[PDB]
Image (tube, rainbow, N blue to C red; front, side, top):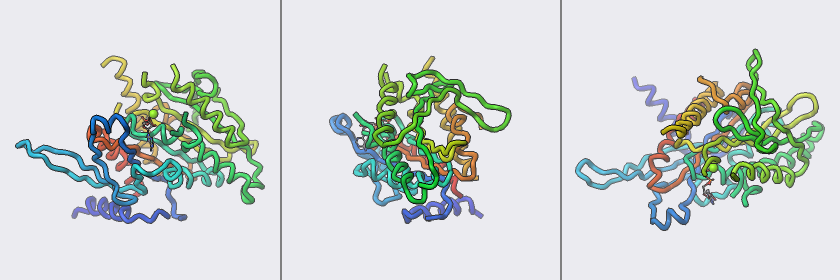
Length: 337
Ligand SMILES: Nc1ncnc2c1ncn2[C@@H]1O[C@H](COP(=O)(O)OP(=O)(O)O)[C@@H](O)[C@H]1O
Ligand SMILES: [Mg+2]
């Protein structure tokens, strides 16, 4: 009869109680939304907070609406996600239920990828790079735990070495942020696999190391506006035991999703995001793009997980961008079903 509506509802319930242990089931895909709090500006123009997250996996959007006759009312729309962080959640907290549970996956010899997605000024970079910033952001934290996991009994007889790469994608091709924005070439041989020629891998033996690389890169990404907010940032943690690659973790700081003549470039951002969504969806089982081309191998393997973190500015003034972001997340999530 209406099984299609039934399934989507069941789905909504299954996710609505949410046992954070969601564990050794098989969860290749993780979707989490995160409301930031209102900043100073927004508070000064006395902007309205239209987001509420009453439970750990239920976000509500109090979108404002006018009746044809000008009457005011609210369309309290409710969404659900594996995990729903409020404005009080610190990075570490967010990091714990998102990026953390994936580290192990690179050690088990898998490939992981965590994505920061949302409108511009929502939080993506503040979450990935750090609130100067680094060391508090997910790149750092994730690094920290990669070492703590390497000198581990179980992972000691592995003899692995830790490597890190930092690059940005902006309108076609790649630019290494660790080799002075040196533009790089992307090739695809005659079987499925892509390769970014010239990407610089830096050996790291300490969290303080990876934090140096992070500052350097972020330094060559925000100095020279609002471009950073129009490029894809991608930090990689790689594990080699000499020979091939053991495991790989791709942390990606996406460009505004809310994105004339040259501004038409937003079409490249939108193709990528549409590409991403389909690759991710392919995982739980389409007009290529640079981004999804570079991270191709991290979606095709069977031993590969990924966590999407949808950032959200709570201001009423961003309501329509919020809804956009949520909607996009919704489709990413119901990929596990
Ligand atoms: N949870 C948070 N706690 C404190 N400051 C935050 C938080 N999230 C975002 N911010 C602040 O908000 C701004 C927007 O984030 P970034 O600047 O992360 O934007 P975007 O989502 O465009 O990458 C930054 O000034 C950052 O310091
Ligand atoms: Mg940003």
